[PDB]
Image (tube, rainbow over the protein chains, first blue to last red):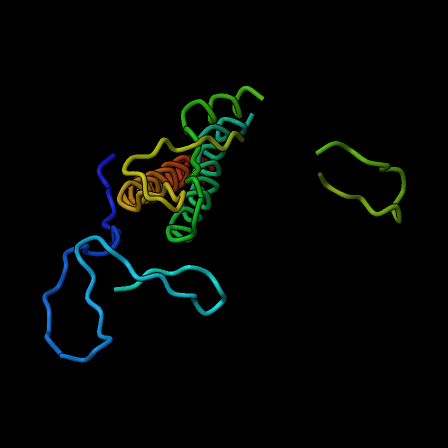
Length: 50
Length: 120
């Protein structure tokens, strides 16, 4: 066995919190680390967003 | 008598069949899962020299109708599409088999021409 192949992959997403812009808008919400807002998705299901 | 030409003759014939086999290997060198085949010359030749069925063969107008071991070639370098034709091996084998076919042609030529020279 000499041949090995080189498939690519995306092991997920980078859960590193990006940094913050102070917009002063009353309802711009920033989550703390490893926190998610829940959203009713297109089909109707709880997706998670930042 | 005059079956003293048999050996080389049949040997030559066997080589020709081998070519087809080897030729097929080159033709299907890209198809998936071909599992390159070949035959072993020496044993096959010995067996054929040691040695379809006849149908209803009374007078004419009854339409007579006529009716080797293809061994795996053990591969190397597996290739994920089942194709085991290592084209390099087959190229070498094809060159050698063509050469030995030429040798057999020369040997039959020599035996036949010796026979003809004695006869004139």
